[PDB]
Image (cartoon, rainbow over all chains, first blue to last red; front, side, top):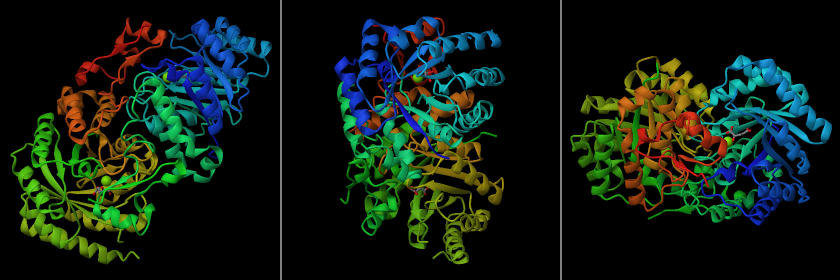
Length: 314
Length: 314
Ligand SMILES: O=C(O)CCC(=O)C(=O)O
Ligand SMILES: O=C(O)CCC(=O)C(=O)O
Ligand SMILES: [Mg+2]
Ligand SMILES: [Mg+2]
């Protein structure tokens, strides 16, 4: 069934955006606004990055938000300790691409970090991801995921370089689901270098993924990851009842403006839903249809997301 | 095999962009620049739109470009006459969604318009599309395409409202290929309302499509269609030899600037390849990899497209 949640990573992946320079107060404002919106998880930079990243994690995790606050660390004993001490509700392990590949060792090293966390904070949710998941040799990847999955709440896949294709993502998520079973959750994180972050997230869900990483406006390393708004536009057309129940969709314009303001960008003219142009109609044969029925050339209603259409009649 | 061509529609679909107001000279400049780039087709607004659309079609078709110039008309006898008289090298018929549906009639009406064109201009390439192809009842759609295909050079599919999913596009293109046979070309046109225009174009090609519609920066009705640059980024990662042979890729920045300048927009901060941020790296563990190998977190080389990476070390 198509049930899924969003992990916002504006305060993690989004910090890796070129122009991101979030004050503790910027982060709190973003987190509170995402919580009001209904977002299920808020992921934050590793506490090990700096004394300020640690403090921010500590504060965000203690905000009393309905959303779970989770932090993203390298899969190391070092960083695990720091992470649990911050009070986060979840820890997202990333086993980085080093790595040749000795698999029961990798399995041992992962299970150890995971074991410490269960010991030291049994109520913290643990996710395990290998970096560059879609480009790793698949037998070894599945071998590691299959062995680690009984010990974790979730496994993730990361299209780190933004080159995975929708059918590749669908296929690999299906194989992961087959080896981890129905209980373990499956998270997808995808970069947008080839314009496939939204499509891939969607195919990931169709294949059984339960969690999708987004950032507001898609901010992140390079051209960033799956954007919150474009993702909701995609999901809304397919599950409109579900999506409108889950989230305060009319808040999207303000989330996009807030982050645009803070990182010093303009909202792209063609940005999903909230871009200057998202609902503009011009062709005569289009306009003549919008008068009998606004739906005729509209994928979704603009009022649902708190915006309006423009007609260009001249 | 993965052979395909691009039909640029900046001078057709792109004219339907909210802020598009192209002078005859703007169009000539765009067309010449696309021709230098290596684009195979340039599609232009219907000559029936206004006396100026007719003139522009006439001029563009007579520029002596290597690219074929083709015009997009309603599937009517009226408009066909006007179209051949302009000297275009191709005519792209669109049978609009009216339509209930009486199929041998629709087939008769289409075959007639097509027959006139063969009579009056036997060297003109004819494409047939039904509007809103992915949402039409499939048996009737395939019935019409199958009957019309022996008489045309190409059939197209249009995701008019921008809601088709990548696996739906793949499937329907496969079914169309099955009924039209290996000779007739297959064109895909997709809107970006749900962030799937690039993904869909790519899946269309994997399924056997031979032609993809793009506009520079994706300008078009609403948030527009498959953007030239994001499409090339997608294809380049998969067929780098082929793509770099076909097109002058280092011209992409200037094509994007030219159109941004003319329609009065800024290039999106995260725009594929040419956006301010397309090649910016920040995370410490990313930067430490870019020094040993720039490829480690880069989908494609920036110099290939005439741009540079940015490192954010502080
Ligand atoms: O752990 C993850 O899923 C994401 C880490 C990341 O930014 C990437 O691999 O692209
Ligand atoms: O004829 C076509 O393929 C495209 C016409 C169009 O703009 C659409 O259906 O979205
Ligand atoms: Mg990432
Ligand atoms: Mg269109």
